[PDB]
Picture 1 (cartoon, rainbow, N blue to C red):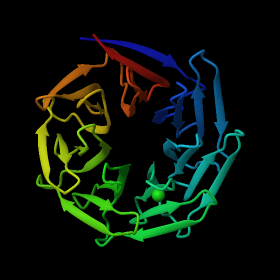
Picture 2 (cartoon, rainbow, N blue to C red; picture 1 turned 120 degrees about the vertical axis):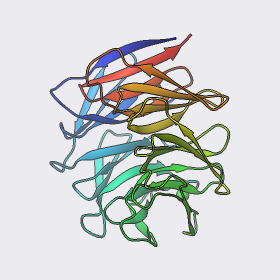
Picture 3 (tube, helix red, strand yellow; picture 1 turned 30 degrees about the horizontal axis):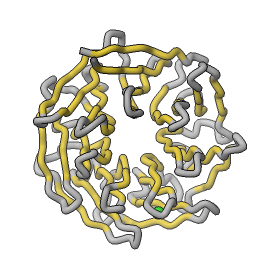
Length: 293
Ligand SMILES: [Cl-]
């Protein structure tokens, strides 16, 4: 069993999507229809940051170690940044229609991101300089990206049916997933030091060690359409089932439990865990807060 609370956001049908939480306790969400980033503090103050570029399709975000928020503008071909001063800088990608998507901090503190349509991994510095690494197979659709325990970046190749690894020097290794045409999407680092990902078509959670060894676990609800995944406490992983309106949990003897979301077309997207609470973005201008026990 489990407890759920909600946070209302609603300037209208804003398309809440990506979510993260500061160690300050602040939650940040992107809102792709409203074209904005919102943060809510624990005392409930909300700040909405309209993007300078209209119809930018803001997708994913991350908080860097120095506290700034970085994000991808999927339709506007840009990486954005909200500085500590609350000012937004954007940086335009060198090739057009790159469709940046996933975003994460790397081992030396640069910001790394996938280009879905550009078929590249990007890298940007403090000072806005961009470096990019072309993927070997065309039409790979690199999607989510995370830092692995090996201090390499790991990402899903949604249409090449593989997990890629890229080191700080740009060396790429692709591990083919054993479930054909499985559609990997979310990936994250587990506390077991492997990477864990979701297969949207496969209806599986996957695990890949930093040496490339892949195991899979069948999600009980058919057509669950999992999307994002995050580590929990211990060896727990938590994931969103957009298709089934549930929150999934991999706990433990690699059992998958599911917790149905009491509400309507929640269509959960992003997910984050803060040591006690599972936070997730929901389509209907809300954020969910889930807790066990
Ligand atoms: Cl780095």
